[PDB]
Structure formats: structure tokens, C-alpha cells
Image 1 (cartoon, protein in one colour):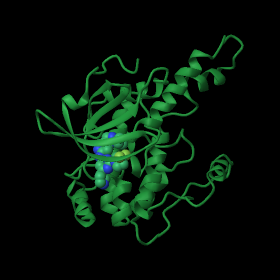
Image 2 (spheres, helix red, strand yellow):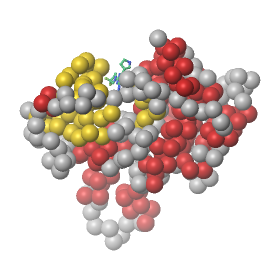
Image 3 (tube, helix red, strand yellow):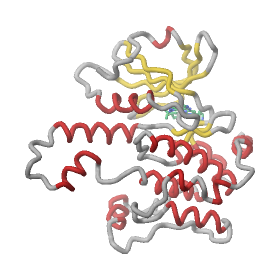
Image 4 (cartoon, protein in one colour):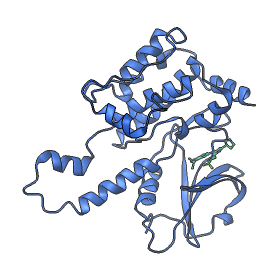
Length: 290
Ligand SMILES: CC(C)n1ncc2cnc(Nc3cc([C@@H]4CCNC4)nc(N4CCC(F)(F)C4)n3)cc21
């Protein structure tokens, strides 16, 4: 069973499907309207047929259903009907920051600062629940028509959670196992501070329209990160960005996770604590988009 609180009913009983927004491996996403309230929602639809593995989708719903924070996309339930699973969430009309910057070009430093503050608020909340997003990037940061910011797409987090559960189930007898082996099996080998690194990369992505080393073979990038002399990336254009932005990048991209600042600590950084960071900055961006 995918989730103990699934609605075993047709989502079209409650929603009018307005537009297919896209589709791919993850399934399809629709813009729909609540037939009673008139509110807009996003519906993510995925095939869910007998003997399919439910574990990843199970974990994705578990994450969404236990979040109640402005900067995490709101969850309105899931429907299982005729072997299709529909996950219902708050609608963000502008899509992702990647959808946006592919049209607008690079964001301003103030726009990036506001985005980073809102993402850090969401991350601090997730981490206080002992959740890890694990896929912070422009494509997974959504913007609604009011210029508000919501973290979404917990698919990678759910995949990891499901793999972690499978490796507990088949770990075997533990009595000869080294503690570090047990720790990797139960906890994964890293912690929530990976999200802070990913936010730093995302800030560069919003500034430059690509993450660092985007044109290097992915396996080479992985290898380079494991060398003892690996150097964190930087913003390319030194004069375009303030010292505060360069420092935000420096500290979020701290190589050692033992020394990398937490989300709460980062919320005190000059870049995201400065005045004038509000949704008007992103409404400006959406006006440029149109
Ligand atoms: C991550 C996804 C399942 N998700 N989760 C919650 C959520 C809330 N709102 C949206 N909103 C939007 C808006 C737009 C706008 C149309 C025109 N420009 C962007 N596109 C899209 N997507 C095109 C590609 C897709 F995967 F189908 C989605 N989603 C998507 C949402």
C-alpha cells in the first residue's frame, strides 16, 4: 500500500483538470481547480499498477504529508484511482526558478538573496524534523504568482529514504559489523548539511545559469570531489557581485561537513539578513518573464 491515508476515489470528482503542464519519467503534472473552493492545485500523476514497487512514492508522500511550513509546497492528499496515483499539492504558477531563468537570464543579487533566505527557512524547518531534501537546485525551487518561494520535488529524498529502508531490511546479522558500516547502512554516510552546500551551488546557478563544472563529465566531477585537494567553486565574475555574496558562497561551500554552517546559522548571514528582501523582487522577475 502506497500510503495509509490515500483517497481511494477519482480525483476528477474534486478537481477540474485545466492543463497538462508536462510529463516524463516521473509521470505527468496537471494544473487543476478545486470544484468547491476554486483554488488551483498541482496534481502529479504516476502509474501505480499491481506489483509495482510503491516504496519511493510511499516515502515521497510521507515527507509531504508531515510538512506544514510556508516555504514547503502544501500537501492536499493523494488519490489512487484505476491504477493511477495522483499527488495533490499547492500550485506554483511560475514553475521553477530554472523555468524562469531560462527565459529571463541571470537573477539579480537581491533576487538571489531573497530566494536563498526563503530556501534556508524551508531547510531549517526540514532539518528540525530530521528530514533532508538532498536535491536543492533551481529546478526544484518553485515560484507562485505572488512571488513566494516553495521547495518541492522530494523525489530524490524519497528514493534515498526507500533505499535506506531496503538496506536496513537486508543488512543481515550485525554482530561482526564495524560501527561505521552500521552507521552508513542506517544513516547514509552524510547529513543534512549537504543541503547547505547544494544551496550555495544553486546561488551560483541563479547567478550564472549553470552550476559549476556543468560542462565536465559527471563521473569526472564526482572523482574530483573525492580528492584531498578538491577546491570549492566560486562565482566567476568577481566585480559583478558584492563581497557579501562572495562570502555567502564561501561559507555555504565549506568542504568539510563538520565545519559547514547550519541553515539556522546561515539565516544570520549578511546576504540573507539585509533589509528589502521580499516577494516584490520576484514579482519584478516575473514581469520581465512576460
Ligand atoms: C515538481 C512538480 C510535480 N510540482 N510539485 C508541486 C508543484 C506546484 N506547482 C507546479 N507548477 C508548475 C508550473 C509550470 C509553469 C507552466 C508554464 N511555465 C511554468 N510548470 C510546471 N511543470 C512543467 C513541467 C512539469 F513537471 F510538468 C511541472 N509546474 C509544479 C509542482
